[PDB]
Each structure stands twice: as structure tokens, then as C-alpha cells.
């Protein structure tokens, strides 16, 4: 395993083998590779176009080096992120409804800019994002929800932080977050930012060992279920990968005006979310529901997408209540309430 | 000039504008860009494939930041790993008989095959201060410009190139950044692909005439064994030209006779060639000098240049002694001569 050899291989645009990639990612994540080569490799990897074997090798490296808690039965809802519009953090609200019907081990992080990351939104609601493993398991048993902070459960990732920071461009690490759940959740609704990554990440998930994971791409260009048009889906399980297309109306709704679904900070997201829980915002609430509908289908509790949206309707009703208990047990209820107020409670 | 914008642009595999690439190069060569980004940038450039404008941009940048001296009237024979003897250095010597030569070059990484290694083995003092450089060109019509010193800014990208260990855009710029700003030049390239690219870049670097060549089986000089693909670049345009060593009238030289494995051995073969004691090497020296003579427009064709070179090689040893006597140690040259 020589870095220089791996780099020439990449310069020649030839894909890496699984364990070749896994040893490369380990060396990188452990801080054994000079910053200059980590840089060259990440750029070469992206310009070559990372492959299935690459993604799988890196994902397995990160899982090996990660801090783990056990909750396979749990479900996660994390997208890749991607550069785009900047819609409201549905994966975080959709995760609140889901705790009402199944343990949720949400994997997330802080966003680099306007605080569009789930860790920022949750912090805005008053949640204590730093949950040690012993207590995390405790919180999932009492509230059926726990937030797993990437920077906390992947301490070795601090070894690639400066390079990623300095480069300032997306790399292979920006699509690995959702495939590296510290609780090893076997169910997941992974949002992807492009129809290509849809196929790439699905073939990779197939070899990552999930019971059922659904990857989705939102028609506008969103890493979530599309509010306006079709939603391209991939449902991977131990028995294959199903392709599924879906318009917003198949849920029994009329196109949700994007204008109302856009946010420009962690607080506006927190506020809008709550406002939807308070029934004071149809659109944002309808957006949350369609996303929750799919997550429910992945749990195979609901056998249809229209049905899932319906059950999500019931769920959102106990949502603020659920949110209150979640925060009061691990966080500051004060903020939550000053937000309920800023969102008219 | 925002490096992240440039980076993203390269990541999307799109070429840069000339001055966009020039500002990027100036910032890099000035050491104003974190190593992490210089690294990402060089790698993106290589993987995207450097275009004409990026080459021009970088060359113009190194030219401005380089330690300069002025001898536009001079010619240079700098090119861009078979171990063949360095004929551009010997060839530079013949040319100094009829025109000022400002030879730009570095040492070879490996077994001293670089112009600087050969010259030093001949007894020449390859480290020539810029103020002394122009005096030596007036007095002897020849001077060697050690790139490593005439391009001090390059230290800002040394650690990065060292760590990457792969070729970058920098491995092909040297010949386009002559410190004396020589307008006449013969520059070898190591692949046909670099012929088209470098010729188009060179086209825009303000030469009076530059001849680019690629010789089989893969040499940055005129092929002594077969074809030589050549690009004649000038204000009037780019001439595509193919050639065969047999058009010089000679028979293809056996490659084994041109290869050396030592700086001193290369010095010895050049002198034996100068003494009439090695036809093959001297034939390889003359076919290279012939194209350069054509670059200076001293001859009307390659055949005339070859015969002209015949006359120049007969005088090159004494010329060599004159050059070294003014800058270097003639005792080292008398030693190389002792047994050649
Ligand atoms: N997209 C993610 C999902 C989960 C954890 C981290 C990330 C991240 O981008 O760092
Ligand atoms: N960006 C990430 C992706 C996956 C795991 C951890 C991180 C992190 O920043 O700590
Ligand atoms: N590698 C180079 C290319 C051009 C000019 C100088 C150098 C140098 O190393 O000094």
C-alpha cells in the first residue's frame, strides 16, 4: 500500500480495488498521509470520478475507525448535502415524526456556511448535540430518538479537516456521511444530490450491508423528496435494487410552491419546522410529510406512498409534543419555547 | 483572482483564460497559496489536461518573476529518458561560433545527463551570476543559464512537486522561460501530444522563430535513427514538418552508440566527437545543429545546415576552450581531452 503508487493509478484514471481503497482511506483518516498527497488524492478521485469500490472502501474505513453504539433496528434520514437552493431541513423534522413510530438514530453535522446542517438546526431548537455513547443509548430507549454528531462519533475525521477546509470543494467525504451511521441503523432514507450519484450510491449501498435503504433525488435539484415534480428513487435491500419514479401528486397533493420552502439560516429552518408542527404552515408541513411518507415505506410499515403520507398526517400532530420531550430530556427547553414563540406558539 | 473559483473551474474540466492562468501562476510562484491548494491545482491541471492558454499563462508568469538579462538576439537549444548523450549542449557550442547562445537548463535528476551536469564535467562553472552572464555572452558568444538559480521563485513550489512525485505543468515550461529572453530556439519535447500543445503556446510567446521537435523512438531532439516530427513556429504561423535522418544524407545511427551513463562519459563522447574520434556522436550533433541553423535562418534547408555544421564542429573544441577559459577550469577540460 504505497500512496505514490495509488496517486499514479488515479492520475491514469484507473479505479481502485475495494481493500486498496479501504487501506487508502484508513491511512488518510489516521493522519498517516502528508496533507499535500491527501489533497492530490481527493482531487484526483473526484476528477477521475469515484467508483463503487472506492465509496465502499472509504465507507468501511470510516465505520471501522468510528465510535459505535448498537441500534440496528433504528432508522436514519440523512442526505449528502450538495450545493444548491437551500431548502428547509426536512430530514430533521421528518426524523421527529419517525421517532413516534420507531427508534431513530439521526447522523448529522454542522454546515459550513449559513448553518443548514441538522446539527445546527437541532442546536437552534435547544438540543444538546454532543451525546456520549452511554447516554445516547439511554436516550433512544426513552425517547426513541438520539442525534449522533459526526464530529463526535468520527473523531479520526479531524485528521482530514484542514485539507477539506482548505480545498473548499466537494470530495468523496461529502457523500459518505449517510453511509456511516454510528448506530449502524439498517433502515435509511438517504437523499442524494444528482441522478448519477443515485446509481453510484445505490450500487455502493447494496454492498454496505443495509436491510433496506432508499436513496432519493428531488426533481428541482434537491437531496430530498421533490416538492414540485418527480422524485427519482432507488430502493436497495439484500435482494436487489428497485428503480422508482414518483411525482409529488402521487401522494395526493398539489405542487408545493418552492418560495415558501426556502430558508437562509438554521433558525429560520427551526422556526419554519416548528410553525409546521403548530399547523400554522401547510406547505412546509406538506413537504415534511411527503419525506416522512417514504421513510415509513422503507420501514415497510406502510405499503403505499399515499398511505404513508396519510399516516404522516397523524404523526405530525404528536410532533411538537414529541419535540418537547426530546429537547427537555437532552437540551434547553427555553430556546425551544422562545422559538415556539418566534414562530407564534 | 480567487483560487477556489479557479479550482472549481478546473475540477469541472474547463480551460482557463490566459491571464486567469497567469494570475494563478503568479500567486503560486510567489508562495501566496497554501500547499494544499497548489497541490490540488497542479493535480486538476494534469488530470484535466493543460490547454494552450494555461501554458502561455504560466510561462508569462515565470518570465516576469525570473531573474532576467537581455539577449533577445541569442538562440537557445533547451528541450524538455533513454540516456542518449546531451547534444543540445554540444550543439549550443557549435552555434556560439556564429551567433550568441543563451543556454537555459538544469541538472538531471538521475545520472547526470543534464546540460548543467555535462558542462560542469567539461570544466565549465555552471553557476553564473546574472551580471557576469551578459559580459560572458559578449566576450564569448555563449553563456549557460542555470534555471534553478535564474528562477528562484520556483522554491515556492518545490516541496509540493517533491511530495507529489508526478510530472506537472512545470516539467514542460522551462524551455519556454529562457532568462535571456532569447527569440530563437530549438526545443525538444518528449511526445507528439506536447508538440501540438507547446507549439500553439509557443506561437503566442513572442519568438522570432522557435522550432519544436519530437524524434523517434521518443527523444526531445532530432531523431538520429528515424523520423523527427517538427513544428516551425513564427510570427507568420505554425509549419508542420516531418523529416527523416536520411534527409541529412547520412545513414541511421545505431542508438546504442549514442547512450551514456555518466556526466563525464557524456563529456568524453562530445569531445571525441569534437576531435573527429566518434562519427556517430558528431553526426547526431550535426543533425541537431542543422535544424537550429535553419531556425536562425542561416541556411535555406536541412541539408545545407548539416554541411554547415560539419564546418562548425571542426572548430568547436577550441571554441570550447575559449568559453571555459573565461568561466571555469581549462585543466578539467585538458583532462577530459587527455583521454578522449
Ligand atoms: N451529510 C452528512 C450526513 C451525516 C453525517 C455527516 C454528514 C456530512 O456531510 O458531514
Ligand atoms: N464530514 C464528515 C463526514 C462523515 C463523517 C464525519 C465527518 C466530519 O466532519 O466529522
Ligand atoms: N523545474 C523548473 C522549470 C522551469 C524553470 C526552473 C525550474 C527549476 O526547478 O528551477
Image (cartoon, coloured by chain):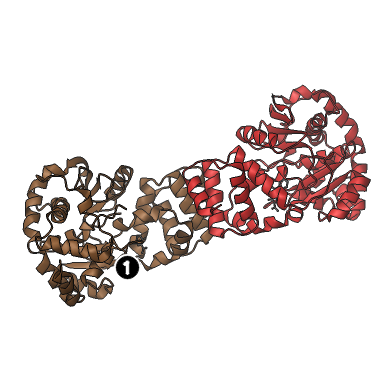
Chain colours: A red, B brown
Determine the quadrant in which ligand 3 lies. bottom left
For residue B231, side relative to residue A138 (left or right): left
Reply above or below: B136 against A86: below
Residue at 25 percent across and 75 percent down: it is: B131
Which chain is home to disc 1?
B
Residue A171 place in picture, x, y as percent: 60, 47
Specify the quadrant that holds the C terminus of chain A. top right
Reply above or below: B94 against A286: below
Q: Residues within 10 Å of mark 1 (few under 14, many from 20)?
A: many
The residue pinned by badge 1 equals B150
Mark 1 and ligand 3: say if the CB distance to the nearest ligand atom is below 8 Å: yes
Q: Secondary structure at mark 1?
A: helix
For residue B237, side relative to residue A53 (left or right): left
For residue B218, side relative to residue A249 (left or right): left
Residue B107 place in picture, x, y as percent: 32, 64
- In this view, the residue in front, B202 or A259, is B202
Instruction: Say whether residue B99 is visible.
Output: no
Amino acid at each position: 500500500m504505497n500512496i505514490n503508487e495509488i496517486l499514479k493509478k488515479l492520475i491514469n484514471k484507473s479505479d481502485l480495488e475495494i481493500n486498496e481503497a479501504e487501506e487508502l482511506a484508513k491511512a488518510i483518516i489516521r493522519g498517516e498521509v502528508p496533507e499535500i498527497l491527501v489533497s492530490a488524492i481527493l482531487v484526483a478521485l473526484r476528477m477521475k470520478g469515484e467508483s463503487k469500490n472506492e465509496i465502499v472502501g472509504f465507507a468501511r474505513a470510516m465505520r471501522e475507525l468510528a465510535i459505535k453504539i448498537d441500534v440496528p433496528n433504528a432508522i436514519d434520514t440523512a442526505g449528502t448535502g450538495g450545493d444548491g437552493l437551500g431548502t428547509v431541513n426536512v430530514s430533521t423534522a421528518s426524523a421527529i415524526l419517525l421517532s413516534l413510530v420507531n427508534p431513530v438514530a439521526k447522523h448529522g453535522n454542522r454546515a459550513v456556511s449559513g448553518k443548514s446542517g441538522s446539527a445546527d438546526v437541532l442546536e437552534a431548537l435547544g438540543y444538546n448535540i454532543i451525546v456520549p455513547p452511554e447516554r445516547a443509548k439511554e436516550l433512544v430507549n426513552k425517547t426513541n430518538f438520539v442525534f449522533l454528531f459526526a464530529q463526535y462519533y468520527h473523531p479520526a475525521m479531524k485528521n482530514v479537516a484542514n485539507v477539506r477546509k482548505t480545498l473548499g470543494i466537494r470530495t468523496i467525504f461529502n457523500i459518505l456521511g449517510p453511509l456511516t451511521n454510528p448506530a449502524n441503523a439498517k433502515y435509511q432514507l438517504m437523499g442524494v444530490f444528482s441522478k448519477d450519484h443515485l446509481d453510484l450510491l445505490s450500487k455502493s449501498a447494496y454492498e454496505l450491508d443495509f436491510n433496506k435503504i432508499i436513496l432519493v433525488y428531488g426533481e428541482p435539484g434537491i437531496d430530498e423528496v421533490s416538492p414540485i415534480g418527480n422524485t427519482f428513487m432507488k430502493i436497495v435491500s439484500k435482494r436487489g435494487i428497485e428503480e422508482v419514479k414518483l411525482n409529488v401528486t402521487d401522494f395526493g397533493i398539489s405542487p408545493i410552491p418552492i418560495e415558501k420552502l426556502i430558508v437562509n439560516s438554521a433558525e429560520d429552518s427551526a422556526i419554519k419546522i416548528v410553525r409546521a408542527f403548530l399547523g400554522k404552515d401547510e406547505h412546509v408541513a406538506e413537504f415534511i410529510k411527503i419525506n416522512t411518507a417514504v421513510a415509513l415505506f422503507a420501514l415497510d410499515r406502510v405499503g403505499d406512498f399515499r398511505e404513508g403520507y396519510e399516516y404522516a398526517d397523524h404523526l405530525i400532530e404528536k410532533s411538537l409534543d414529541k419535540l418537547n420531550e426530546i429537547i427537555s430530556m437532552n437540551g434547553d427547553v427555553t430556546k425551544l419555547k422562545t422559538i415556539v414563540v418566534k414562530s407564534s406558539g
